Image (cartoon, rainbow, N blue to C red; front, side, top):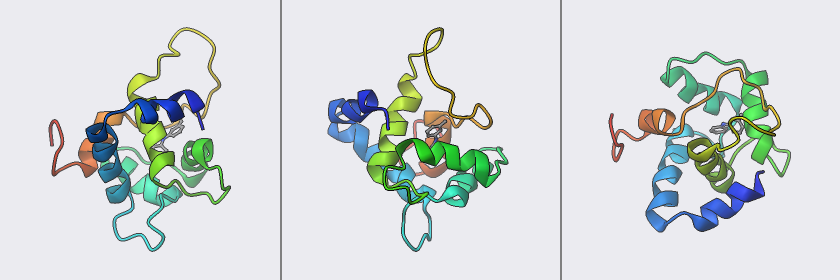
Length: 120
Ligand SMILES: Cc1cccc(Nc2ccccc2)c1
């Protein structure tokens, strides 16, 4: 979990984290635990035209998966959210978390966010 971004949620406005939450919640549409498992994650990706495999998906979850549960919950999602929209490490040091299927902040969000999305 990028503690830089982990601060950035601490740095996001109320609206900021509120919006992002929704995407989490809809990422977990009908989920029993309501945390994003790999196929919960994969759902949205396929909602975006992606077609991951859990392996890929897991590495996305694994970042913030502090409990080692294989599921992202809100703040876990949220820090990736601000991570996704910032990702300032363009041409310098960063560790690769599988450039397999990279979900875009808004593009992914919009898939869930047919409710308060910038687009639809
Ligand atoms: C490469 C990488 C690292 C961390 C997170 C994600 N994406 C993601 C998006 C939504 C839910 C879970 C994960 C991708």
